[PDB]
Image: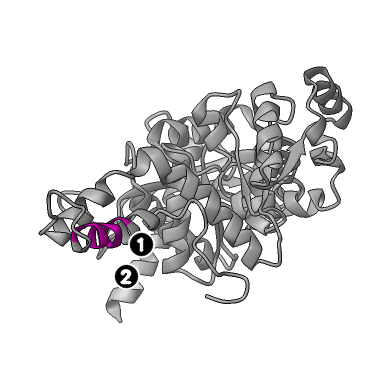
Amino acid sequence: LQTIGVYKEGIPAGLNFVLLEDKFLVLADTTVNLNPTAEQCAQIALQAAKIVEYFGIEPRVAMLSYSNFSGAEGTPRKMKKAAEIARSLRPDLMIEGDMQADTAVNPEIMERLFPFSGLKGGANVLVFPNLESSNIAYKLIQQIGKAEVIGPFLTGVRRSANVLQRTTTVDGIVNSVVFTALEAQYIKEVLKS
Amino acid sequence: FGRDYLIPKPFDTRVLLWVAPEVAKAAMKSGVATRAIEDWDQYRESLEALQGPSKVFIRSAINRVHQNSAANGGELPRIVFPEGTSTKVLKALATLVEEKICQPILLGYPERVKEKIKALDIPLLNDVSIVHPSSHPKYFSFVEKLYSLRQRKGINLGEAERLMADPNYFAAMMVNQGEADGMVSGSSINYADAVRPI
């Protein structure tokens, strides 16, 4: 971060993929920001989204909270606000909050309890309110869930650089370096332009 | 001024200011006065001072509400009282309807409130409308409304339904939608709880 730094208006943020059978989920920010503001969570969402678009998928973004559309003082208000900002910056996307994680990933729950929501078809981008929640989620899913998890991938910086989780296995590193290669190529190209 | 108004009304606060100085004029001019009033305005001032709000404010208030009623085709304001089983409220309503202040609407289970009105021997409120929230025609319409305004403030349809059965929320909504012109609550509950749904 000191040498390469963030690109314009970007925010350094760690991002993981959960590779499920029907979909993949993006989790952010899993590594950098202890307690990002609404404004930061919105920017994180944007970064995640553009990455999802690189893989030809429509991003659908949920700002996670322990709450369902309450916007109460504290994290609900932060995530509800983040969703509002995100929506203003990327008016074409489904971005919604505040909501709990199952409400977010599960479209049936969303329709049954909160049909007013603008998130339909389940979210594939999950942005977290704080580093405790994101870091613990991706590590837990990776260990006890029965799904491949790849990352974290450092987002927000000018050139291609990624930091492994030290708990990584060798196959973990193999996967990570694959995506770093992908990124490296992308940035080289764009530059070369 | 007209065929239906030949004189001031009895409790008109202006009677003193116009009559007392003209009487003063007649007393001084007729020579029966022994101390002349010279400063006519200081006197009119002194006269205004004698009938201040402590004597007349509520008098004028009730008069004004009545005149409002007359100008509105005789329609009284519908004021809903969600604590329909409160004895203070009922006792007040005896006087209030007797002196034609409003059209009270009571909220609660009809049996309980009619038992209460009988227990207290208030015969003047046997005509007053009593409604059980869940059993009103516009109930579901109301819940929808609440939902739409508070769906992103911690209230979904389930919760909206649950709350609208609360007499406070129901009174509030009636007033909001114009199915009542106003509401009075808080006689038997702390102020925060009573005022919050409003």
Q: Residues within 10 Å of mark 2 (few under 14, many from 20)?
A: few
Q: Is residue A6 left or right of residue A38?
A: left
Mark 1 lies on a secondary structure that is helix
State the residue lying farthest toward the front.
Answer: B31
State if disc 1 and disc 2 touch (CB < 8 Å): yes
**Residue denoted by label 1:** A184
What amino acid is at disc 1? Ala
> What's the residue at 35%, 62% (across, down)?
A184
Question: What is the chief secondary structure element of the magenta stretch?
Answer: helix
Q: Is residue B125 left or right of residue A87?
A: right
Q: Which residue is mark 2?
A: A188
Question: Residue at position x 56%, y 32% from top?
Answer: B194
| Residue B122 is at least partly visible in this image | yes
Examine the rendered structure and indicate whether residue B95 appears above or below residue A38: above
Residue B15, x across and y down, in percent: 39, 57
Residue B181 location in percent, x, y?
Answer: 64, 54
Query: Where are the magenta residues, as a range?
Result: B20-28
Q: Is residue A121 visible?
A: no
Instruction: Tell me which chain the residue with mark 1 is part of.
Output: A
Relative placement, left or right, of B97 versus A3 is right
